[PDB]
Picture 1 (cartoon, rainbow, N blue to C red):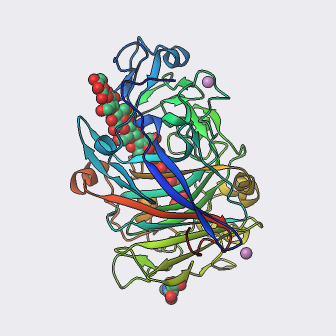
Picture 2 (cartoon, helix red, strand yellow):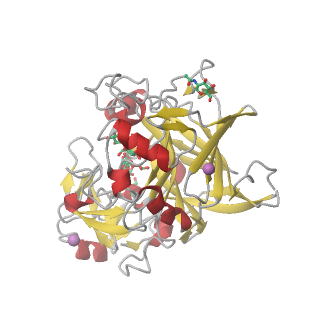
Picture 3 (cartoon, rainbow, N blue to C red):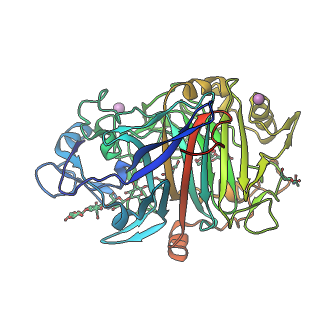
Length: 434
Ligand SMILES: OC[C@H]1O[C@@H](O[C@H]2[C@H](O)[C@@H](O)[C@H](O[C@H]3[C@H](O)[C@@H](O)[C@H](O[C@H]4[C@H](O)[C@@H](O)[C@H](O[C@H]5[C@H](O)[C@@H](O)[C@H](O[C@H]6[C@H](O)[C@@H](O)[C@H](O)O[C@@H]6CO)O[C@@H]5CO)O[C@@H]4CO)O[C@@H]3CO)O[C@@H]2CO)[C@H](O)[C@@H](O)[C@@H]1O
Ligand SMILES: OC[C@H]1O[C@@H](O[C@H]2[C@H](O)[C@@H](O)[C@H](O)O[C@@H]2CO)[C@H](O)[C@@H](O)[C@@H]1O
Ligand SMILES: *[C@@H]1O[C@H](CO)[C@@H](O)[C@H](O)[C@H]1NC(C)=O
Ligand SMILES: [Co+2]
Ligand SMILES: [Co+2]
């Protein structure tokens, strides 16, 4: 897709800190950009939409190539249309924003410049951030994660994509998403099937795959940490159901691991660690700090801080495994206890290390789940399972929770605030910010 300028594109600024082993942190200045799917897509020569509701213009978009040549992405009114605002080192995303139309959440990427994404090399380093999830009830997900996206949004690889990172193009994740309107410089109109429950979405013939590191997927009820390996580390197109993931009939028939080696304290047995109120170790009605460390062995460590008290990731006992570190033994024990084999089939942490060794783009999003109602995160899943089934219970939410139309109507004012992002070598982010 090309870029049009009927509406100006001004990326909201966002500062963060880069720390060093020497014990000092320095301020960096970046900005955020909204994903291309949220934008107005219209003809390059007029204001006629190329996409409207959940269908494509059959004349402007008869096929993937022609559509890309005829259509462009336009600017976004961040605050008024998408409920996205920033202030210093803080970013807030509103759940439902009402303007000309109704908008639900957002997916944003951290930029290095106005035209490029900021790339982070996680291996050997640690990432820290403060988060307020108090306004996120059952069914919602305020996420912060990394994906192996190209710094330019794919422009250098795909000439027909001239909009680039400035317009939030190039997304990919372990689900090999097929809902993306533009992939590899082309539209995703061929094989397009409109969603039955979402008036704005559909599923196309192609998907976009890549490694994904889910640092944080959570609400006030549950939280999970999950690495997802893929046989191909970076962004790669996929065909139909061979994509696997949430958008295909076969979830595990692809090149990426859509499940990952997840670590949810509640799912692991500690139902008193994270939740709303003082009866939990970490009170989700208050802001907290989340620190994730990527050691060179490929293992991942985690600790939290609230009101100046530090808590390491709670110990878990699963099969022959015991400890609080996400390593090869944990992931193997999890597959043995909870079942499944996609993580190991995709290479596990060894394959995943290839992603963290390279650059990864930071993503912050707020969304509700039109496919599984977020039950996999905060309820019992599958819903027909009982508490006696290992790993079925992931949270205290009712199995009837998370219906999009319902949560959007009942909790429109929900929101998430991410702030004070700090990145640097292991053991450095806890030091004084510059
Ligand atoms: O027409 C002439 C006038 O145009 C005006 O401009 C309009 C334009 O016409 C109109 O088309 C445009 O409409 C856009 C809406 O403003 C916008 O809200 C809407 O956003 C949708 C988006 O369509 C949809 O693809 C997206 O799907 C989400 C999904 O909800 C979410 O559950 C899922 O979540 C993932 C997470 O993000 C991720 O972190 C996690 O790992 O996985 C999750 C599961 O996959 O993500 C998908 C996206 O991949 O939802 C959003 C939000 O509801 O998009 C509309 C276009 O399709 O609005 C323009 C502005 O009003 C001009 O302004 C006027 O001057 C002209 O005259
Ligand atoms: O695709 C949504 C969500 O899936 C998560 O994997 C789930 C999977 O959906 C479920 O079938 C299985 O039983 O449990 C796993 C772990 O909760 C995945 O970890 C998320 O990253 C992803 O957003
Ligand atoms: C849950 O984790 C917290 C923090 O590590 C710990 O104090 C508490 O004893 C754990 N509770 C259970 C039931 O394991
Ligand atoms: Co094809
Ligand atoms: Co270790």
